[PDB]
Image: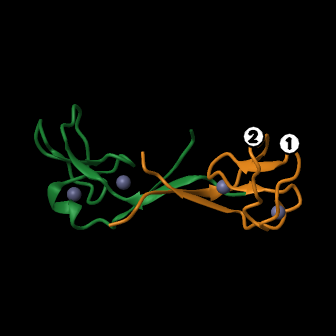
Chain colours: A green, B orange
Amino acid sequence: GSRRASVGSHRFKVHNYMSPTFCDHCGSLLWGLVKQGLKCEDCGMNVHHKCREKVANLCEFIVTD
Amino acid sequence: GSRRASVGSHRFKVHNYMSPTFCDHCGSLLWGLVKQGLKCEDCGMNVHHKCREKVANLCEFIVTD
Ligand SMILES: [Zn+2]
Ligand SMILES: [Zn+2]
Ligand SMILES: [Zn+2]
Ligand SMILES: [Zn+2]
């Protein structure tokens, strides 16, 4: 038995956060009221622009569809 | 960079083939005109009932969505 996972690399896109949100890499607040960071279009990971280069490219999530 | 793949184990279901179709494992014809074998609902692999127990469980396909 195996879960079905979607497995690729992150697809980060600049994102406008509507509530205070923290960087999933470093834990600091994503500062500002607009374009505060990047959100992975596939797995939802939120990062600072500066942290984009610090995270592993590996992007996986369980497909519960 | 990486392709994105859907990765799990096969999900075989009995299948009615509308044209002559061969087992993707052993290469012999899926005999008969109905319920000739099983098709993986995820990757499309076609197998004899008897070959279901012979194939590796690993089921992957590229997500081109
Ligand atoms: Zn991701
Ligand atoms: Zn950060
Ligand atoms: Zn399969
Ligand atoms: Zn076979």
| Residue at x 75%, y 66% (from the top left corner) | B25
Q: Quadrant of ligand 4?
A: bottom right
| Residue at x 73%, y 67% (from the top left corner) | B56
Q: Nearer the viewer, residue B31 or B4?
A: B31
Residue A59 shows up from this direction: no
- The location of residue A57, given as percent across then percent down, is 33, 65
Say which label, 1 or 2, has the lower sequence index.
2
Q: Label 1: few (<14), some or many (≥20) within 10 Å?
A: few
Q: Nearer the viewer, residue A52 or B43?
A: B43
**What is the three-letter code of the residue carrying label 2?**
Met
Q: Which mark is residue B33?
A: 1
Kind of element beneath mark 1: loop
Residue A36's place in the image compared with A8, above or below, is above
Chain where mark 2 sits: B
Circles 1 and 2, Cβ within 8 Å, touching? The answer is no
Chain where mark 1 sits: B
| Residue at x 85%, y 47% (from the top left corner) | B36
Disc 1: residue Cβ within 8 A of ligand 4's nearest atom: no
* Residue B47 horizontal side relative to residue A25, left or right: right
Q: CA distance from mark 1 to mark 2?
A: 7 Å
**What is the three-letter code of the residue carrying label 1?**
Leu
- The location of residue A35, given as percent across then percent down, is 13, 42
> Where does label 2 land, which residue?
B18
